[PDB]
Structure formats: C-alpha cells, structure tokens
Amino acid sequence: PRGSHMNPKRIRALKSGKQGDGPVVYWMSRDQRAEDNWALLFSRAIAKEANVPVVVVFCLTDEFLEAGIRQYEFMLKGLQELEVSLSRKKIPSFFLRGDPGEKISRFVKDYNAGTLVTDFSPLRIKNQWIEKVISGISIPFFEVDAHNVVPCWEASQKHEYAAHTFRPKLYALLPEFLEEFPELEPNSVTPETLSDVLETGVKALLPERALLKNKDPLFEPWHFEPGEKAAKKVMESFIADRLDSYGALRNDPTKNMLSNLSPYLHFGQISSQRVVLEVEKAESNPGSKKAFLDEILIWKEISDNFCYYNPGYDGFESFPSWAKESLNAHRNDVRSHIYTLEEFEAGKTHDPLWNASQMELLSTGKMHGYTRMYWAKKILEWSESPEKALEIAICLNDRYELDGRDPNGYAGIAWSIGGVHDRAWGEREVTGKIRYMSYEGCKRKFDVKLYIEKYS
DNA sequence: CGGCTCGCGCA
DNA sequence: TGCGCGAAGCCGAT
Ligand SMILES: Cc1cc2nc3c(=O)[nH]c(=O)nc-3n(C[C@H](O)[C@H](O)[C@H](O)COP(=O)(O)OP(=O)(O)OC[C@H]3O[C@@H](n4cnc5c(N)ncnc54)[C@H](O)[C@@H]3O)c2cc1C
C-alpha cells in the first residue's frame, strides 16, 4: 500500500477491516529502533497516504520478572534514548504496562486508531498476543518483518532441515530484498514515565540478583553500552578493526574477535540488514566476509524459520527422529556425573573449562560463541535426562544471556542438545549420536588456560 | 548418491 | 597450528 521503496512482500495483513479515521498505531515489540525499521517506515507510509499521524506504542509486560536486571536496564535504557530520537521526528511514544492482549485493544479504542502495525516475532507468546488483539479491535491489522532481510514467510514455507538446503533459497532472494533504507520522514500533524518504570522494575528484581560470596553483584554492565547510537559504534568498530580477522579467530574465546552485535540485534537496537549492507560494501578478507555473512543471514534467519514452523521449539519433540531415537535408547545409561540446576548455575562442576564458561556468562552476560556449544553439550552429558538438560540449558541461557529469550537461543540450544540443523555422529554413551565435544578438542584449537584464568 | 557450521593422527 | 580422514543419518537433486 503506497510507496516506491517499500516491498509489499514485507507486509502481511493479520485482519481485514474498514480503515479508521484516526492515527496509525505502530505496536513496537521486537525492533526497538528509530532508523532502519521497515515496520516504522511502513507505518509512516500508511499514515502519509491517509493524512494521519503515526504513533508508536510499547507494552511493558511482566516477562521481565523471569529475566534479571541485566536485560531490564539494557532494554529500558535503550528505550529512553529511543524516546528522544522519535521525539525529534515529532512521533509520540506511549509506554503501557500490563497484558498486551488487553492493553493494546484498549489503546486502539481510546486513541481511535485507524490502522495497527506490529513487527514480526516467531515466539509463541507474540502469536498469542496478536490473536487476542484481533478479537478486540475492528481496524486493519498488519504485520511487518523488520528483523529479517528476507521476510520469514517468504524465505521458506516449511521447516528447514539443514543450512545447506536453506542457504541457496536465502541467497537467491538477496538481490530483491537487500536494499538501502529510506529515511524516516517526520510527522506533519502532531497529535508512563520510563524512569519510574525502571526504578520499580529493579526494585522487584533486586532479590533475584546474581551475587558473589561478599554480596557483590556478578554482572558487569560496562561491557556493552545499550542504545541505538552505541550499537552503531559497535558495528563500525567491528568492520574497521575486527572483520578482517573474524574468519580465522571467530572460534578463539581468548580473542575478542566477534562482532558483539547479538545483544543489540536481539532487542532490535540495530538492523541486521544495515549490518549486511555495510559488510557487503566493506573491502576485507573474502573468507572473513563469507563466514560472517553466513552467521548473520543464514544462521540468524533459519532460527526464525525454526521457531516459526515448530511451535515446540523449546521441547524434546522438536528434535529430529534420528536424534530422538538415539537419545531415548541412552536414557538408562549411567552418567559420569549428575549435576543440578543450582550447581550448573554456580559453576560447581568438575570441569574448570565449563565453569569458566558459566562465569563469563554470569559476569559479562555474553558467553563466547564457541564455548556456548561446549557449555550446552556438557549439560546434556551431566544431567538426569535429555528433557532436564534442555530445561537447564534454556533456563541458564534465558536468565543470564543478554541475547537470551531469542530464536537464536532456542535454535542454538536445540542444535547443541537435539541435533537440530545438524547431522548424526559417532555413537557414544549417554549422548548417543549427537555431536560430541571434548576438553582435549578445545585444547588443540585455543589456549584453554588463558580462558580459564581470565574467568577464575 | 553427494555432502553436510566434531575428534584425531600427522607435518 | 592446518589438513585429511573417520563415524553417523538424511535431505534433495534426479
Ligand atoms: C547453546 C547456544 C545458545 C545460544 N544462545 C543464544 C542466545 O540466547 N541469543 C542469541 O542471539 N544467540 C544465541 N546463540 C547464538 C550465538 O552464540 C550468538 O549469536 C553469538 O555467540 C553472539 O556473539 P556475536 O554476536 O559476537 O557473534 P558473531 O560471531 O559476531 O555473530 C554475528 C551475529 O550472527 C548471528 N549468529 C552467530 N552465530 C549464530 C548461531 N550459532 N545461531 C544463530 N545466530 C547466530 C547473531 O545474530 C550474531 O549477533 C547461542 C548459541 C549456542 C551454541
């Protein structure tokens, strides 16, 4: 609907109806940014055609109680900066608290909304909120994929078994969907405190804070400055200083050669399409560029495909049949070690390498990409059952990772424990044919002692 | 039938 | 360190 630089395949209608006379309402959930936001740009285009203002609404749910302070402050501080950024474009921002199914329905009626637009997320709870809103409103409802370069329903129509079958499909659609972002035109017609929401939330999460023996907090918040502006700086420094050596040193946890974009990419503080555009134009190592593009395009967006077409993405049923049969047969195998959630959480295992991986997660909130596999696969080896291992890994991932509660997390954990998007390997006790990682294998690929000594 | 995002022996 | 082989089931081009 209207616009020359807007691909209609990025927008899909969730509910048809007569368009109202009021402003266009953008229900911002996943892409918390002002620039490079297709959902915000599309909302502005519909508003321009209808000669109505565009507004953004945010619903603060009770889900932050399941998380900790580290995600709350990171997310809330970025929204404060986003509030100023949208204010400069004469776009008002309304921050609501409560159930989005009931709050969004009330906001549309009270504000006399004409059209409702929201971003795309394949998570279960997002689909539940959308259906609740659909039953309570009478205006057109649209959904825009502002997170993936190629829209999730357009890249593939089915669950993808592996990357090698999804890679040609994604790369074929890149020329159509990889394009520059038009600038966000400000509003022409003009028409809760975030500080109070922040101060209340930390008070409710203070008891659940991760502490040391001397009651000192474990989380170090100076490693990643949140916000749209800081996310851009991280991207620029990656291309200039780190992209060249990414291809060779991405699997070395002792070297800070990763992009460190996942906390911003999870909260939508930066667009992966913007990152792809800058990386494509960069003159760097061709092997490094191909390796990084495979990470942010194929593996990031296949995680959306996994969650979109598998409602049980965080369960044992989502595993492939070969993986399920292999794990089932080894249920009665005697485990070399039985560890509980608390012992995993405190880093109280016999493995100093695994403990150091947990400490990096506890202290920085972002464990290195390579050690994340060894972290999750040892949980399977040292748990009562595959279901318990899946529960433990998801719990610690979602509680302590800044990029937690993300499709990349569920696909990554399902890859590690259930062989999702993987293949079978040598038969072993307990883990069966799931891919095996050993402490000695990590020794021959990076300096394990340096990584251990860094995080005690 | 070819080829998939580990460990391991060997220079 | 970097390279080639081994051990496993299966998708997808035909
Ligand atoms: C068990 C396990 C759990 C995971 N949990 C999370 C999580 O909670 N949140 C999360 O965002 N990612 C998760 N991943 C994926 C991966 O660990 C992170 O994306 C990455 O380590 C974050 O660091 P980075 O952005 O600097 O990595 P980079 O090497 O710089 O990667 C760049 C971007 O590519 C994407 N990406 C890279 N590797 C993967 C991957 N394996 N799967 C999917 N996308 C990928 C991410 O968007 C990332 O920001 C997990 C991986 C594993 C093995």
Image (spheres, coloured by chain):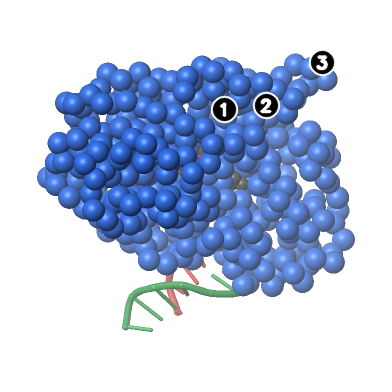
Chain colours: A blue, B red, C green
Above or below residue A160? Residue A136 is above
What is the spatial separation of the Cα atoms under label 2 and label 1, in whole angstroms? 9 Å
Above or below residue A202? Residue A123 is below
**Chain letter for mark 3:** A
In the rendered view, does A265 fall on the left or right side of A350?
left
The residue singled out by tag 2 in the image is A205
Q: Secondary structure at mark 1?
A: helix
Q: Secondary structure at mark 3?
A: loop
Q: Residue at x 62, y 41 (%)?
A: A398
The residue singled out by tag 3 in the image is A214
Which amino acid type is marked by label 1?
A: Tyr
Q: Secondary structure at mark 2?
A: helix
Counting residues from the start of the chain, the first of labels 3 and 1 encountered is 1
Q: Residues within 10 Å of mark 3 (few under 14, many from 20)?
A: few
Q: Nearer the viewer, mark 3 or mark 1?
A: 1
**Chain letter for mark 2:** A
* Residue A327 visible from this viewpoint: yes
Numbered tag placed on residue A72 in the rendering:
1
Q: Position of residue A413 (x, y in %)?
A: 61, 51
Q: Residue at x 43, y 20 (%)?
A: A80
